[PDB]
Length: 492
Ligand SMILES: [Cl-]
Ligand SMILES: [Cl-]
Ligand SMILES: [Cl-]
Ligand SMILES: [Co+2]
Image (cartoon, rainbow, N blue to C red; front, side):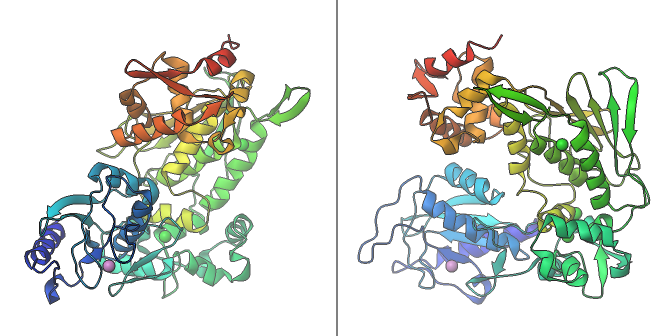
């Protein structure tokens, strides 16, 4: 965009004033954000910078969210003391920092190195977000003066609508508070105890659905107002191959929230749920992890085409314990079947944010990732999500009885907190297939850069099962430790 050029220019300017160990601003370049790599100040003397620094990554990621959240975005110069303008510098690795910020904030800003008085500095260019970006502490604030204060979704959106890109699902409609069904509102309340203390009006407005004139946005209308049509429906089969045993189609006068619930409800029943025994300790386990299902559901309900008529077609196969979710629309010109687990930009950012506001979905990648994890963790195969001729996007979850050996293999992970960890899940999975694993394979697996790969591998190298690490190094590759191999030999 033309904004970027303006921003890069401003930075060049600030840097050109370099003299006497510090830099200065001017009315034109007053908004540039001067930041100093945190965790290096000792008072009298400042420590040398390293290529990696998680503490600094945290603070910086939080700052990027301020920026991206304020309209027009802005630029940051890491390595310049705030207010004074004294050059400090930073040796943070670009790729590391980019990937690091992206992992905790959900955005990968353009960062470029620069050299002032011989010192190195990072120029970070962050663009305006199409939806609020919550920081590491789940806060939503934007740049004001040189500092940045917090803002509610209500204000954030009216401003986004006004001076920002076009979010179709955020546009104003003719729907008013009187169009919101009490049933839908009731649902929102039983799903988030926070709203409990406020009225229907201040609720819808709190989540950014309700205008200031009293109008609902397109995402607000779609969620709390009947869309006089089926949004999603279920068809229970006996076996992948036809012969419909039964179908549950929600009434068109229901809002998406109502329709979503109606499907979830009936789905909870179809998901039979059988009993597994471990050391005579018997526990009820559904054919497919509840989370995995609801995750797949909300996912379609949020990234659906919504402009198409045909409802999200969700079918359940009895004898195979598998659930298929076909959604109208296809991967946007950019995303591919092998570039989804990394994608973060939703079709309808406005709609996505509204679901977040209601507390019905996680940041984003967390969703699909927790889904994958939940599958792998029970020894099932990862949920496959490919594009079907239509356009259509179907997600397939194949479940059934859990595989005991795998359960215990995971049950024996240490630290305990690493059991439900997505990284060790992917890593262990790649090794369930391949004999050896390389940093490249781990990468293509997580569908992420080489940084995430190194990270996952490391965490797995430090994980322990039966007093031995998960993976072990040999030659120039990595491979499952005999500890696990012995547990997995008892499969089939
Ligand atoms: Cl369920
Ligand atoms: Cl949108
Ligand atoms: Cl919204
Ligand atoms: Co600053």
